[PDB]
Image (spheres, coloured by chain):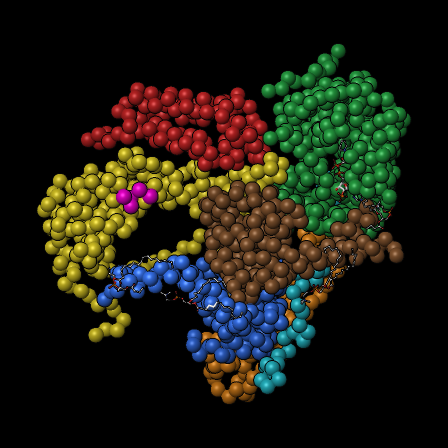
Amino acid sequence: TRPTVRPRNDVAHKQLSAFGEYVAEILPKYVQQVQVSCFNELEICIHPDGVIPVLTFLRDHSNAQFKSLADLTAVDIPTRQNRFEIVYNLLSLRFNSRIRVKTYTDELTPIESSVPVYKAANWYEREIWDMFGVFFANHPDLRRILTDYGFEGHPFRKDFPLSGYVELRYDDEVKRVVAEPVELAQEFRKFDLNSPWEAFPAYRQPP
Amino acid sequence: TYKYVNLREPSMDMKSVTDRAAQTLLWTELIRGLGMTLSYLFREPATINYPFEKGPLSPRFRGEHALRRYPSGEERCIACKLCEAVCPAQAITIEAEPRADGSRRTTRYDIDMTKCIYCGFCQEACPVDAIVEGPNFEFSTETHEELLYNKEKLLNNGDKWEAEIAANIQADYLYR
Amino acid sequence: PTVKPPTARKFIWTNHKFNLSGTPQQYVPYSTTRKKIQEWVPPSTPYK
Amino acid sequence: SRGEYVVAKLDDLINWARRSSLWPMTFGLACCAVEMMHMAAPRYDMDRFGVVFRASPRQSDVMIVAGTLTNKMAPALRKVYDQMPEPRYVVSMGSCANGGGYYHYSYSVVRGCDRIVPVDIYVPGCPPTAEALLYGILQLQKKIKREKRLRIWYRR
Amino acid sequence: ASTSVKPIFSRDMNEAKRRVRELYRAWYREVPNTVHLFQLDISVKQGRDKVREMFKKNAHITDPRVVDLLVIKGKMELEETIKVWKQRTHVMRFFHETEAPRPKDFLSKFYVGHDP
Amino acid sequence: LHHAVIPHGKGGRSSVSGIVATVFGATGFLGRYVVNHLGRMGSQVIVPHRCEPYDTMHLRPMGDLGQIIFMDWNGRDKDSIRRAVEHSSVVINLVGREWETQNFDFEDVFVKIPQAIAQVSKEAGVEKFIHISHLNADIKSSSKYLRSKAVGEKEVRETFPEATIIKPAEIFGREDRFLNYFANIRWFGGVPLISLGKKTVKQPVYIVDVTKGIINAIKDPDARGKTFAFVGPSRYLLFDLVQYVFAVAHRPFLPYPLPHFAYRWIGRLFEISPFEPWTTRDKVERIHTTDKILPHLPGLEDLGVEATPLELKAIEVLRRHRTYDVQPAKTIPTS
Amino acid sequence: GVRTSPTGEKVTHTGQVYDDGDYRKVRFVGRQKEVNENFAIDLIAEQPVSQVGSRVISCDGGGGALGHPRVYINLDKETKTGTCGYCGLQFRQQHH
Ligand SMILES: NC(=O)[C@@H]1CCCN([C@@H]2O[C@H](COP(=O)(O)OP(=O)(O)OC[C@H]3O[C@@H](n4cnc5c(N)ncnc54)[C@H](OP(=O)(O)O)[C@@H]3O)[C@@H](O)[C@H]2O)C1
Ligand code: SF4
Ligand code: SF4
Ligand code: SF4
Ligand SMILES: [Zn+2]
């Protein structure tokens, strides 16, 4: 074989492709796209209205039994109308398999909280609101989790500066820690690392 | 394969029940614990007599940064900024210009030892073994400014520790 | 070092110095680059 | 005996008492606390120098800031410094406490615990080895050994 | 379909204004407790003026969804103050007591530096 | 001059303000606010200190890296003064002690030391020089503290003619000895006073107001060779002022008269302590001295500072004196 | 080597020295200015020009893999020597 190239597993790829169609046939109302990657990962892309139907089916259906929410996060892609892409990574212990479910929202459109399906989603959705600003409807207790109290903005957005807008310091006149506009003794040095030559022809986007 | 850690059924015969009754009333398993601490009292402690004895290290130890020279005294650094580009913490600031004799050399080489994570990526990325992490780990200061190294400080560290840096590199360059 | 002494080089320190922090011999950082922008010096003779 | 001789000796006695009984309060915030625990472990045994393992904030003489100090945590670090009886010294352990470290440019990180509290010793490393931290503590003892409070008072 | 946007809480500005006044009433009555619990040096009048000023900034909004988020954020901010999750530093960051006044006119900005 | 220090930045911690200041006596009550304000705007501050370095640790956080430099100096060593000012563009003299020691008396700290600092600064080429006198300085006053203030204020005006002299009233603040002084008398039963506090009028000023006046006098070219008088916005009788202090502190107020000669006898007893005396014969004279009115001198309003009333910030100072609203005292209308 | 300026301050191998009127000289008061006494520019000038008998020569800086990337230097010009771009050693072609 080739010592340095990752071996392929066509059996898992075929199995996940068949199961992707299986879900798409059972939830046409919501599924918008299904794809399987070259390393055997299945992604189900759905309408944001189908969060509770699709996740509930995947958790409870006998042939799915995805009873674990491994991770719930979001990605900011400012070029899209709906900036944020909400990603649910699920694990099935019954079938020793994983599935990824993706939806989308924007700054003002809320998404239905997944706490009714998976209790683990409670703190993951608090982090998405805190870092990305996506609002989850009917969340039992939604509020900042990671950032400081009174922190303005949502750091993990692509238009939020790396060092933020304010910085802390102890002032002896007021005898407390104060917040002032950020000044850096050394500015972060922006490196332009991209190579002007195409690396992967297989992903060439048509002009 | 798997195994159960706590799935035993305590035998309920009279002898076994009385064995547990003696354990409860006579504190047998608690005294068994005192035996273990008593034994440690009579072992030799593992403490070393610092600073008169020092903990063992290896040639690969990543300590204080330093700038080296060739056997002639010429600086090894030729201002290529690979250490600056790789440094994950952006702790290295470099400026360079053609020297008086026309050589490619730095006019500034600062390592903010308070941004540095002592990762060693600088000594890996250097193609002339100029910047290294020496074996000194005792250079704590009394002020924050003393940890902002410039080229003069880094060259002095190289001249200071060249006797030990060279022997460490000699003992490890074949693994690199 | 008595059995395998280090390689000798002219630039290596002959006298080793311990940690000098907190003493007058301590290191003080400074910029090692010369001035960048040369400012205009006005003429020293009156224009009129 | 001259007054300058009695005061010189009293300084040594109180300096000796204070540097021989340094009880530290450790702010274990991040990985540097694990190396701080290795200084208390049998290998180095900080306790044999007179440095008790764990001391309450109202009994401590030195605060060891061992780990990243974030904005959210900075107010509580100052609150513990203000409640520490004097003399009180502060030791900054690691790059994160020193000057921000790996996370210098983060929106949520205090770029050095020395802009929240005064610092007496800076221990460099990510993390400093248990021996490099013990060097800082022993370096703080020598700093306390050079104090001349009574001598300076006698010349006012 | 372009403007057929899912709401958060309010279906029109009339409902959104209802939540704002309820939020304003909650803040108005809380200031005397905040000035007492946190031992602030400001007065109740100054605290309520800041509450008033904060509401006035977002008075030009006409999108109910945007108003819903401002009320959602406002309630979250109020929750931190009521439950004493904030500290005196967080409550006093609305007043900018250590930031020297910055000039607003052209000439004063012209002397100090280059920022417009 | 090839160029000044050319301020850069936004005026924050990491900016460059162009001020290189040698603040003498920066380890006291007034100094810890001057360094704080100079450091907040990014100024190189040299802090000559006579004390142990442990007592200057509260200043280190006030400036960015390298913006605060600590040097040793002796009040009677002109060479040490020269080392601290020869690179500065402004020298601020805050040296002052409210009691006489075995080694330094009111003549040394208020005449000789200010004059030595002023002379060396002129020789070294220092441009700005700010000297802090007292408002009630008078060569014919019962307080040796105030008499030496007048003598020293005159020699500074001679050695360094282009010197800005600030003449503030009693300053009240967190670390003051004016409002904290009218709170430690409760430990002795009652609050003894001369003439029951009547016949004495005081016009205290806030520490930050004095601090902003000094900062604005450094940056104001129209302050060279000018004598300022920093006073508060209201005048109070010494009786109603002290009554207000005890009302903010919620402590019993039992003011009783005490003859002047007896107040001196108790004052002498407290002078035997080798530490900061609780009260000295000189302090009692100043507390009961009446704040002068000098309309010809400029004040805070000229430098651009609005004097802060004592009512908005008496709670700040006196919060620590409470155990486990208050009516403002009676002001004195300007005729 | 280190040559002091007219104010008592040493000039570093990069030519940096604070002007007489610069306020930044204050940081050295009571302390010292760290300057490295071994100027590399002068030291590399003490190395003799190696005489070789071929058009092209190779330099790795000495020590094999402990030196610098091996480069090949051309010696066709008789007016000047062949200088290594990394270590500064100079080479000359013997009488041709
Ligand atoms: N505090 C007030 O109410 C008033 C009212 C009007 C005028 N003043 C004068 O302003 C100067 C500042 O005084 P202060 O800061 O308020 O009070 P102090 O704590 O005493 O500060 C004195 C500093 O000067 C140092 N100092 C005193 N004596 C000496 C000396 N012989 N040699 C060197 N320094 C001396 C002192 O240092 P240290 O002893 O604490 O280490 C302080 O730093 C003052 O002139 C007022 O009269 C304020
Ligand atoms: S050890 Fe790593 S972080 Fe430190 S200077 Fe070298 S490359 Fe940068
Ligand atoms: S130290 Fe090495 S990697 Fe860094 S600039 Fe110099 S030659 Fe390049
Ligand atoms: S300095 Fe290094 S070890 Fe210490 S907290 Fe920061 S990253 Fe962790
Ligand atoms: Zn070479």
From which residue to which does the magenta span run?
Answer: A119-123
The tint chain F carries is green
Which chain can be seen in red?
E
* Residue drawn at point x = 75 percent, y = 24 percent: F190
Q: Quadrant of residue F187?
A: top right
Which chain can be seen in blue?
B
Q: Residue A160 or D28: which is nearer the viewer?
A: D28
Which chain can be seen in yellow?
A
* Residue drawn at point x = 34 percent, y = 27 percent: E67
The tint chain C carries is cyan
Residue reaching furthest to the top: F335
The tint chain G carries is orange
In this orientation, does residue E60 appear?
Answer: no
* Residue drawn at point x = 42 percent, y = 60 percent: B27
* Residue drawn at point x = 59 percent, y = 39 percent: A171
Where residue E5 sits: x, y (%)? 24, 31
Q: Residue F87 or D148: which is nearer the viewer?
A: D148
Give the vertical position of F322 relative to G74 (above or below).
above
The tint chain D carries is brown
Left or right: residue F184 versus residue B23 is: right
Q: Quadrant of residue G40?
A: bottom right
